[PDB]
Length: 294
Image (tube, rainbow, N blue to C red; front, side):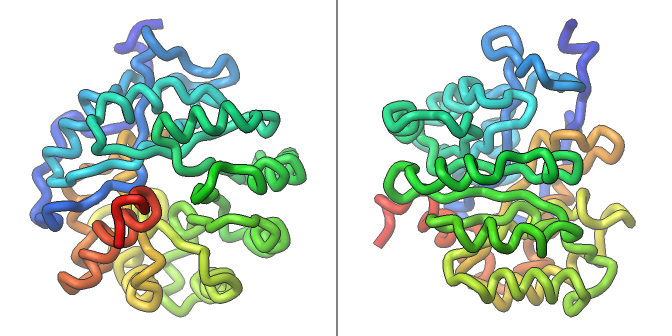
């Protein structure tokens, strides 16, 4: 079925951000969908998205004032990382990636992903998936990744505690997407943020993405609960925080964010030039372009 018949989840004319990022800023959480003609979606994909290919992504990146991207395998492409690899390739060195793998992936295939620009893998623990997930296989694969890879994990606040033993056993660094969706209504010292800080305090090498006010804050823009709840977290873990747009906003078709306003959250959660530089340049450079650092 045609591009037009598929789901649009992004703003096609996003606002210019009022905020200007530092010259070398990195959007560490974005995606491509297709284009379907070259890169089809997983047959298990329920609700197919419109094409959001690499040319759109680079246009977006330029528009928002970012220098680099980390392109995270989209879930509608399952195990097949082709679209993402292609986009990294077209990025002319301006992109790295996160993959989603079949736990049965062998050493040579992972090496091929590394040369393709992949620097980690993703575990998506949705509420409907957590019970059914093969967690043992996830751990095995996580212990034999190429040198210097990390794992990216998404989960909800409701299931953090039951996932503590799994995350403790992960033998590489971990990045938590969207902070594990704490309820930002509760405030910066609320029950969710308390539980999340205990996770962070359990290992030095757990990082987070301070992302997605659109997913976390039901009030909609300017997402004041997100701002007030997330800023103290960013401040308390300045060296363990990265940021992303989440463009093209998978599954956000019911509340499509304006990427201009998404970007304008950055100075609210990171008020100083110093915190901005850490979250948007040096922290993501350390994780995704480590060979370039020092």
